[PDB]
Image (tube, grey):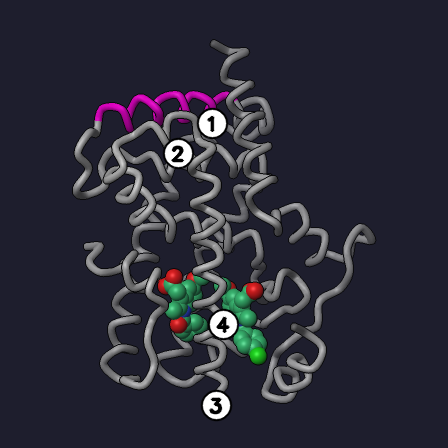
Amino acid sequence: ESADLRALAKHLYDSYIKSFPLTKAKARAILTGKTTDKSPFVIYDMNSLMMGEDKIKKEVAIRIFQGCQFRSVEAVQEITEYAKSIPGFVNLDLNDQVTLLKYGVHEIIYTMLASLMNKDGVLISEGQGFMTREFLKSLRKPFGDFMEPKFEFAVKFNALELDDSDLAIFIAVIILSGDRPGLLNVKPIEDIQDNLLQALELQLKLNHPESSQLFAKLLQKMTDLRQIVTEHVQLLQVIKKTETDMSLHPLLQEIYKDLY
Ligand SMILES: COc1ccc2c(c1)c(CC(=O)O)c(C)n2C(=O)c1ccc(Cl)cc1
Ligand SMILES: COc1ccc2c(c1)c(CC(=O)O)c(C)n2C(=O)c1ccc(Cl)cc1
């Protein structure tokens, strides 16, 4: 079993690397000054944003809005590709596969968003750019309040100091939650999570031997993930009631209508 769990961990990590182009490792190298990667253009005001458009591949709050959207959709596409590699996932009832993805993708998105963040801002455009926390906070209501909750989580979450091999199993654990609403066959989902949970436990113990109860502390973080989703959805509802001229991407619209 112990050798089997390591096999499971290595399998998931390999799938993770194959599925997510911008890893935490790449993100850290960019954010700290490493020579393996190159420096981002920093956007911190209106003119940096204007010049950033020239360097990086009508209202700005709207443009930034539309930017996250395309990125979220892309992320959903990646997380979906990853889930199919989770042993057992494709063998589940198709309705359950959908349900697991529906409630799971945003929790993974915010998890992985933490990798691209520090207390000062977030990587964008596959790491070419960097948007500051304060520029985001300064955006007009309600747009200014969207990102700050993510930062506060990311700051707390990044203190756990997980690397990608850690995250690979954790996101796998998130997808295979037996307590999602509407699931038909909970039992096969829980059997897969049991093994995934076992593998996370051993992975965290071997990769972080000195940080006690990291497993427990990491599982407790799923609480914070939920509140991020709940709060976000409510802020989105304000947008739809106010900006009747724009809409969510169909895929995003399906994920959200009607989650909770
Ligand atoms: C990756 O997490 C985010 C962050 C912001 C998001 C989204 C997702 C989505 C998509 C989603 O909810 O998955 C939309 C549609 N966002 C916005 O409109 C928005 C509003 C204000 C600002 Cl300052 C920035 C973006
Ligand atoms: C999910 O987290 C975020 C937050 C902000 C983002 C993005 C992602 C992306 C997508 C990405 O990160 O690749 C873009 C593109 N964001 C912009 O604010 C932006 C910058 C310049 C222009 Cl012209 C328009 C929008």
Q: Nearer the viewer, mark 1 or mark 4?
A: 4
Indicate which disc residue 67 carries. 4
Tell me the kind of residue under disc 4. Answer: Gly
Discs 2, 1 touching: Cβ within 8 Å: yes
The 10 Å Cα crowd at callout 3, few under 14, some 14 to 19, many 20 or more, is few
- Upstream in the sequence, badge 3 or badge 2? 3
Q: Mark 1 points at which residue?
A: 200
What is the quadrant of residue 38 in the picture? Answer: bottom right
Disc 4/disc 3 C-alpha distance (Å): 13 Å
Q: What element carries label 4?
A: helix
Q: What element carries label 3?
A: loop
- Ligand 1's quadrant is bottom left
Discs 3, 2 touching: Cβ within 8 Å: no
Q: Quadrant of the C terminus?
A: bottom left
Tell me the kind of residue under disc 2. Answer: Val
Disc 3/disc 2 C-alpha distance (Å): 41 Å
- Read off the magenta span: 187-202
Q: Mark 3 points at which residue?
A: 58
Tell me the kind of residue under disc 3. Answer: Lys
Disc 1/disc 4 C-alpha distance (Å): 33 Å
